Image (cartoon, rainbow, N blue to C red; front, side):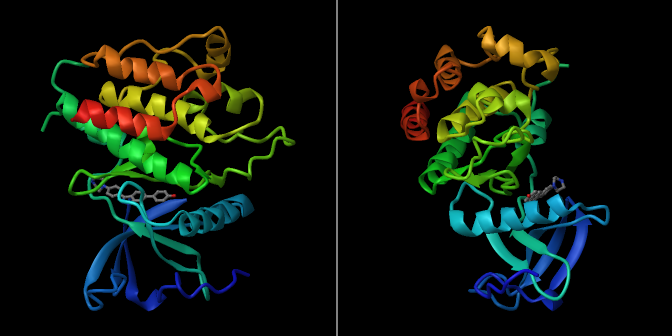
Length: 281
Ligand SMILES: Oc1ccc(-c2ccc3c(-c4ccc(N5CC[NH2+]CC5)cc4)n[nH]c3c2)cc1
């Protein structure tokens, strides 16, 4: 069924599938690193469950193809290889030993809210992620699922944009389907995505604002106490989240600018990068 692409193809005899982290498992990939071709490199492998749908398979194939076209960056989980032939589809990606940003932040919370993090650590985290999105945007990629749970942290605390399952080319949003943007978590979605069936880089900027609010609240849930059923109405009425606890007015203004009603009046990722560098220096 799946064509050949031997630049990306990786032998199935050299992949030992370990414990779970579709389903993702810890694996050892012997010779996946070009410069050390005998050593067992720890990677992440995404595959189908036994109860998978036709959509699950085209989603996974779509995700793989997306990660080949976007290329290489410090602040995105990078495609390492793929087993496409002669058995189950395996999509092989970088292992990030400290897991998702949400649990990473919640675990480092000071006591009494129910290694700790500095203001600068939270600004640095946001800045890493803005650089990741500046690259993705420049590669014509819209992510469509920016959230803390879809950021992974490496052993060295590097922030990696993950879960390209919903990612598209900019020119591959269907204005002429009702179902377009139907599988995006609504609490992270720009209103134009919710309503008008569009999605631009400026839709991702809105999401990145929500990610910022998650970062500065140390892994808090957006619109606390507000059901997704009521959020649609509160947004068109112009509701916006209030400032996180130890967060400066400045970074709150940044979140608020990401949540402008008009997509083209929101800042670009390039502008967020410039501004976050000045605050981090
Ligand atoms: O489409 C997808 C592509 C990649 C991944 C994915 C998910 C988890 C990981 C992980 C990962 C690494 C460590 C953890 N841990 C959390 C901390 N203790 C146990 C290890 C969890 C997840 N590394 N790389 C990944 C890629 C998920 C969906």
